[PDB]
Amino acid sequence: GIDCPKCKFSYGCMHFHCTQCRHQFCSGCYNAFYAKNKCPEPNCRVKKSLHGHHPRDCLFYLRDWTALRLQKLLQDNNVMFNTEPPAGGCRVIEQKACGKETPAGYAGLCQAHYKEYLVSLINAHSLDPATLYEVEELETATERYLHVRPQPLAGEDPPAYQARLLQKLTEEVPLGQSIPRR
Ligand SMILES: COc1ccccc1C(=O)CCc1ccccc1C(=O)O
Ligand SMILES: [Zn+2]
Ligand SMILES: [Zn+2]
Ligand SMILES: [Zn+2]
Ligand SMILES: [Zn+2]
């Protein structure tokens, strides 16, 4: 299940409570959640919201991708993923079974739980979503994680600019370090 990164107790919303230690954290990347006015991070722009600071491969972000784009990341890396239901209506047990509609090609899960499954594979294989980023996404990631505003250099054509952004991001900003890897 999910372990409190603080106490280590084992168990579509990312905000998780551990009742033992009262830690607030993200169930996708295990980074801490902060209530409004409680965030200590100097370069964070969100000071009046309940939030955490997530790596680019947290489900917090990747849940907003389409299933098709999540599949594309897996396909580009030749990681297999299920599309068909199991041998014998979403079975995933939620805290209120999920019971939602089970679309064709979504492996017998609802849309949200199928994306969670794809992200679980993406994370297991340490696939980097930045490899599919358009330049706008690379610029956003640069601002978010490197705290600088990117801009192309004189003499840099568009492919070179995009490649530079991608190279600096991947070299200097690790994927989530508390996300479980295989
Ligand atoms: C799926 O749930 C959400 C998705 C996007 C934004 C907000 C929510 C929620 O209100 C529930 C989950 C949640 C609660 C508090 C803080 C963050 C989140 C979250 O998952 O983003
Ligand atoms: Zn705990
Ligand atoms: Zn997260
Ligand atoms: Zn913050
Ligand atoms: Zn479901």
Image (cartoon, rainbow, N blue to C red):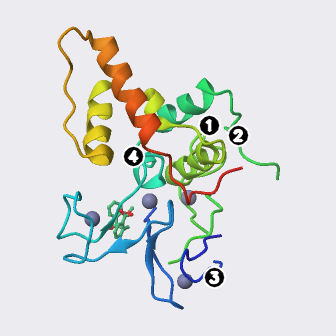
Give coordinates of residue 131: x percent, y percent: 47, 28
Eye-nearest disc, 3 or 4: 3
Circle 3 residue: 9
Circle 4 residue: 64
Task: Check disc 1 and report its element: helix, strand or loop.
Answer: loop
Give coordinates of residue 96: x percent, y percent: 50, 78
Alpha carbon of mark 3 to alpha carbon of mark 4: how far?
28 Å
Q: Is residue 175 left or right of residue 36?
A: right
Task: Check disc 2 and report its element: helix, strand or loop.
Answer: loop
Circle 2 residue: 84
Residue drawn at (57%, 65%) of the image: 98
Looking at the rendered structure, the kind of residue marked 2 is Glu
Eye-nearest disc, 2 or 3: 3
Q: Is mark 3 within 8 Å of ligand 2?
A: yes
User: Is residue 133 visible to the viewer in this orientation of the structure?
Assistant: no
Looking at the rendered structure, the kind of residue marked 1 is Gly
Crowd around label 2: few <14 · some 14–19 · many ≥20 (10 Å): few
Task: Check disc 4 and report its element: helix, strand or loop.
Answer: loop
Looking at the rendered structure, the kind of residue marked 3 is Phe
Contact between labelled residues 1 and 2, with CB atoms less than 8 Å apart: yes
Eye-nearest disc, 3 or 1: 3
Front residue of this view, candidates 157 and 104: 157
Alpha carbon of mark 4 to alpha carbon of mark 2: how far?
22 Å
Residue drawn at (33%, 14%) of the image: 160
- Chain-order first, disc 2 or disc 1: 2
* Quarter of the figure that contains the N terminus: bottom right
